[PDB]
Image: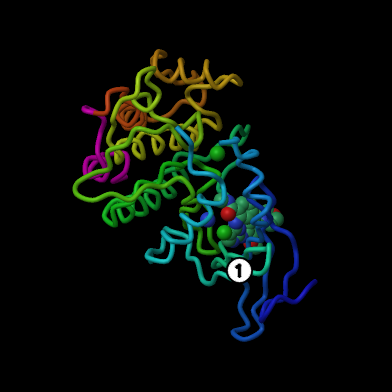
Amino acid sequence: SMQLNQYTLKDEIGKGSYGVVKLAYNENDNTYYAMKVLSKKKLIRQAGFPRRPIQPRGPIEQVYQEIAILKKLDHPNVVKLVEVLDDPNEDHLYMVFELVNQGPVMEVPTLKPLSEDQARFYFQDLIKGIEYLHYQKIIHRDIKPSNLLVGEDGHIKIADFGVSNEFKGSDALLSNTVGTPAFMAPESLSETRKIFSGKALDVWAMGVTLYCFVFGQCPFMDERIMCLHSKIKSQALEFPDQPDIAEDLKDLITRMLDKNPESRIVVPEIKLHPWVTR
Ligand SMILES: CNC(=O)c1ccccc1Nc1nc(Nc2ccc(N3CCOCC3)cc2OC)ncc1Cl
Ligand SMILES: [Cl-]
Ligand SMILES: [N+]
């Protein structure tokens, strides 16, 4: 192990493009937390070498976005940021989260999808979490199974706010394509620069997520980003023969994955859907 301020850093629980996640025991409150360790130089370098004398939110700015956003949130279905250790003289940046003990609900693809009942239970948490974020005027933009952490209590917490957008008024008005390709809504994948609303992007990703829950793979898939984007825009939704799923679940998924955001089901409607109300 190693000591970092009041934390004893132990088992490594995750490693990804961002940085590493360690189990951390806090000696002052005798509680365990997840500590994410990042290098600032590495995040900067990950953007690519700066060009000599539209540009995306670089990786370091995604990290700082996440900090700024999580400081203002408090909901049981959203991961809590507990502390940030950021010395201007150190390269390392440390983000301490509450421990969500079972880790991501699913790696996609999987041969072991969730049962309908487990899918519903987690989906209920997802709805509550997203309804809260939208109420707080945040569009998540990276909803997917791997960003949904299952706690010791069996409930989901939403993570990964790096490409999120805040808005004023009723909705975000967005023109940039960010997040995870398989989960990006068709209206964000237009040839010509267009403006699209934010909340509906999150509903679409929720739909892809719920399809993943019960089927273990995305409804639209291709190893090539550009062909994937084309399938998201042009392919009609299909369900496999097996596993058979309830008609009310197929209806919900169909309505979340309406390609036209004007008619796509909204969260108040999802909360009323028969599959959700059991
Ligand atoms: C967005 N995804 C993440 O933040 C993330 C990805 C991979 C691993 C961990 C991880 N982040 C957390 N992970 C946890 N908790 C985990 C996660 C995975 C694990 N694994 C331990 C080994 O068996 C599989 C589960 C344990 C754990 O706490 C004991 N708590 C909070 C956060 Cl923020
Ligand atoms: Cl995923
Ligand atoms: N996170």
Nearest the eye: 145 or 34: 34
Q: Position of residue 121 (x, y in %)?
A: 42, 49
Residue drawn at (65%, 39%) of the image: 49
In the picture, the quarter occupied by the C terminus is: top left
Work out whether 68 lies above or below 275. below
Would you say residue 53 is visible in this rendering?
yes
Of all residues shown, which one is farthest toward the right? 1
Q: Amino acid at mark 1?
A: Pro
Q: Which residue is mark 1?
A: 88
Of all residues shown, which one is farthest toward the front? 53
Nearest the eye: 210 or 175: 175
The residue carrying mark 1 has its beta carbon less than 8 Å from ligand 3: no
| Rendering quarter of residue 90 | bottom right
**Residue 270 counted in the magenta span:** yes
Q: Position of residue 255 (x, y in %)?
A: 29, 29
Work out whether 247 lies above or below 119. above
Q: Which residues are magenta?
A: 262-278
Work out whether 162 lies above or below 37. above
Tell me the SS state at disc 1.
loop
Give the side of residue 179 with respect to residue 194, left or right: right
Q: Position of residue 98 (x, y in %)?
A: 54, 67
Give the side of residue 28 with respect to residue 203, left or right: right
Residue drawn at (21%, 28%) of the image: 262
